[PDB]
Image (tube, rainbow, N blue to C red; front, side):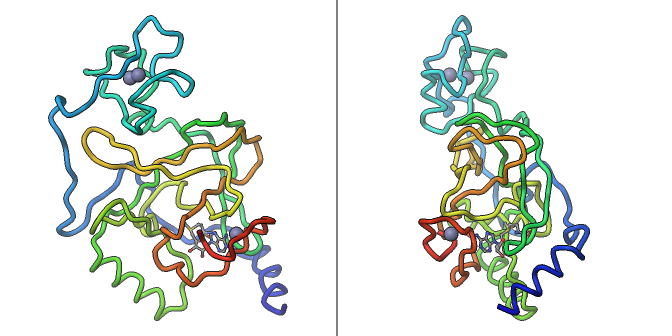
Length: 232
Ligand SMILES: C[S@@+](CC[C@H](N)C(=O)[O-])C[C@H]1O[C@@H](n2cnc3c(N)ncnc32)[C@H](O)[C@@H]1O
Ligand SMILES: [Zn+2]
Ligand SMILES: [Zn+2]
Ligand SMILES: [Zn+2]
């Protein structure tokens, strides 16, 4: 391939990735609503303050089991609650690096335990009409990098213009992280969680599950033995 010879030159030249606005929390756009519930619609888990790790990765916690974050004024474990990861934004340390075939990627600077919260997939929250427009734009300009992930009907996260490090995590068919929809303070959020123990220096990947909007035709370069050929 003469395509490859090109990408070898490229990997040496581009020193920084294209710029984006680094945000902490989803930012709705146009008509897009964000929902809330009364505290009464937030479940109280089975954990106790006296437990060893109340609401932790390895506890019996029904909230964590059913992908509900605890509310700190509702959880019986109180401030000892280890199930407030989205709200608190404590992420493992990570850094951007340049791959050969998959643009910029993300690698951890620390060890990560199986089940650990790694990041939230954060961006602009846009509708289908704004999503179609941005994908049309990118097609007309030979752009193949998409950052769009559906939260629910007519609410799409675009980590492209605005987002956090999660936007640099490539698809793999043999991934070490997984995307999950959690209920947080009465609305949905997308979290990334380690499938296994990950060593410092390793790239962080997830199965896009064909949810990366615009990548429907894209050939997978993950290089795994069981590669599907596609971003799913
Ligand atoms: C959320 S971005 C990930 C970061 C991106 N690599 C960058 O340089 O900003 C997703 C895009 O990365 C590329 N990509 C990610 N995983 C890939 C894979 N396994 N094979 C091919 N391209 C991939 C595609 O262009 C896709 O639209
Ligand atoms: Zn609990
Ligand atoms: Zn709790
Ligand atoms: Zn693959």
